[PDB]
Length: 213
Length: 212
Image (cartoon, rainbow over all chains, first blue to last red; front, side, top):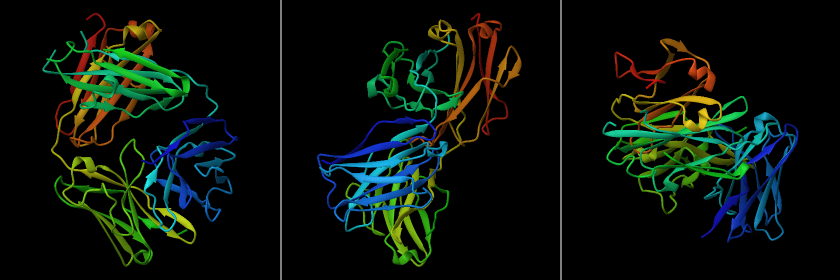
């Protein structure tokens, strides 16, 4: 089974350029259309272009000012998107997607690559447990993830085995540092008789942290 | 330059039928594709070529295309269907997406479940002090938090973030974080956060004292 996988989140200074990879894990990009589709925070999908490797033809949307360059690997396994002269409006999630050459749609999609255009420096998060002040019949716990850059952080409870009752909130930026929080609600008969652990991963700083509540 | 006009929202009772329009200029002679994007995820193809459905997609999802309007039709809608939806065509060597339509599912009013949390030891030890307030599983979406410190409303150092409509119970949730220094936090005793919401005449208030 065939899976598009993109390279990791990126941070680039205003004015520079970013290049992103898209790999057809255990598949191929011959006989296919690959496309790059960006998405500004809380905005819609916008087509940047698409490249057919067999007809060796690239196509681009206007609105990019000749700023996009879409290519592909000689093994014809890997696809590249390149965006030059980065401005702060280029902060976006960049997806690649693949579809049949005969058809007009895209049934295969990468996970997306977050590109953040900023001069700010990388900073691992502080991860604070939120414990029930000082019992009811249901109790809410939480983690506070503070002071990190850039996005993303990944948060889980109990290494993923706890996902029911969870609210993980969108990160918010204040003075170039993000803040994230998450609550999990359990029934008291449960806590603290069982560990409930916050797991925070932050690949930009290579940090994985656990916090038992 | 070819435009696709979707509505920004569609709202449907659970179990009832949702219809999302993709207004296109003579769109009916184009092939129309539809995508679903849940919060946090990548787009997923749910209808291709007007009306064809990839394997894996429920039959509840159905498409049509004629005149100047293509339509995605989701019947017996459940909370799992809450997502942004996009339609897609080709025109003159370019791909075009309509702006997102957000599908929200209806449900009954619910008062916020409110919880307050003093700084952690770890954070006091670092010189920081954050007071966190979760306002959870309420409906409808509009809500307001007020922070009082020793009786007086405080507005600075407050950070807010909202969830998307919950994927299983169709409610909404809010986090509020008031951040001070360990010093400023210890120049005071009473920390208070209060939730004002449609479902109540009086604000729901949680509070604590540094003392205990």
